[PDB]
Amino acid sequence: DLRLHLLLNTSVTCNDGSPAGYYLKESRGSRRWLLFLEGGWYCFNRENCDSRYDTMRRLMSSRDWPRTRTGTGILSSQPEENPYWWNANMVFIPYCSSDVWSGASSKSEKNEYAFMGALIIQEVVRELLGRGLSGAKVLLLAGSSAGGTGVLLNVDRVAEQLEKLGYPAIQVRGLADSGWFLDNKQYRHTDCVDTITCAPTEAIRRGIRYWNGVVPERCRRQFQEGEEWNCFFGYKVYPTLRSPVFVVQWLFDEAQLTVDNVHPVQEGLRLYIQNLGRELRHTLKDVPASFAPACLSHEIIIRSHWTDVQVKGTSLPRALHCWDRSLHPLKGCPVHLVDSCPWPHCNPSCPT
Ligand SMILES: c1cc2c(cc1CNC[C@H]1CCCO1)OCO2
Ligand SMILES: c1cc2c(cc1CNC[C@H]1CCCO1)OCO2
Ligand SMILES: *[C@@H]1O[C@H](CO)[C@@H](O)[C@H](O)[C@H]1NC(C)=O
Image (cartoon, helix red, strand yellow):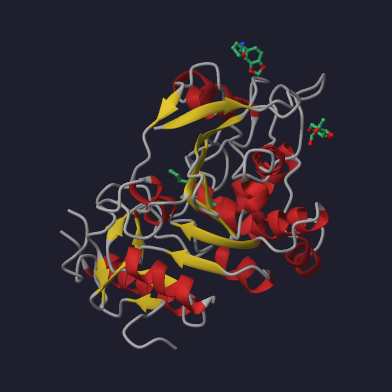
């Protein structure tokens, strides 16, 4: 069980002004720290945030959070469930900012909601340094779905923060799960007039203005004012990052298919699905630490059965261990694992 701590800095809040927080399980014999970012879509204007507050309120408020959470998958402390990092210090950061972890804006006379995702991460890191993170050797910032995109937006800022605070020896790394999306041609098209018809490029462009969203500085300098939405797409922001980042992405991600307006498959949709797999594989060709199986799924690293899927005979926990060794090619210990077969579930280890 990981135990809830609400932030001591009361100015760093969830959407409705309640304090943000983190769940922690310490491992006093370890200098490894895992900080995991929760996912769960986003909201980008007053009307769709109001709807989210009625039926997805745990993603906008700490008012109803439980005192404890059980660690699962990569957050499990049992080697049977977590062969990779079972002895690490474990941190789960709830997603209560609805901003893909990018926002830096308080609730005020002109803002009904606070969007503070980028500042929540910074304050969690700060308060953990007084609870043992000062003695760390490695801090892995991990996350799933919107939290995986959050890793890409924030990992270099965590590295800069620790350097400026006087801890240049802590090695900061990223693990982005199911947060590597394509701004591709959709299978059917709708102009952006409301929540469900607005493609991610248009929704994120509006969201950044609504959230006062923040992107990594080198990527911001490339795309410049008005074009910061480009940095929410992994294949565009990843080449600007300095920290080591491992990319986990299903080739036929269900959330990608949803935003592509895809749900007996005839030729047009067969060609569309096969081309998506090819394009995703192409964007990962020069990513040296990656795990990309040919399955229709979404998220993996905090699932209890995350040990089951394999690419070319190698599991995800093994690939992460091989990554650790490479950051001290390795015989029998690969770090780049991308399926080549062209249809969902052509890999027999795909989750059922
Ligand atoms: C009031 C103002 C709001 C809001 C929601 C509220 C309702 N009260 C929420 C409090 C009770 C428990 C912790 O926060 O959403 C944005 O502005
Ligand atoms: C998240 C973050 C993104 C993104 C796309 C997503 C996916 N969320 C939208 C889906 C969730 C469930 C139904 O619509 O584009 C780049 O940043
Ligand atoms: C609390 O957080 C805000 C927002 O980042 C920051 O400006 C302020 O300095 C923080 N206060 C303390 C005491 O850390």
